[PDB]
Length: 31
Image: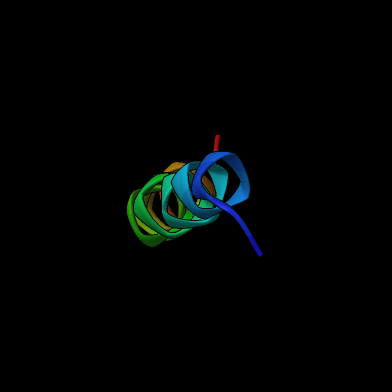
């Protein structure tokens, strides 16, 4: 582990935690 890698880790959680809702609504409201 390290400081740099640690910064990227959380980045994935914050990006995913929010992304999960993206496709969740985008797909649910599909054409």
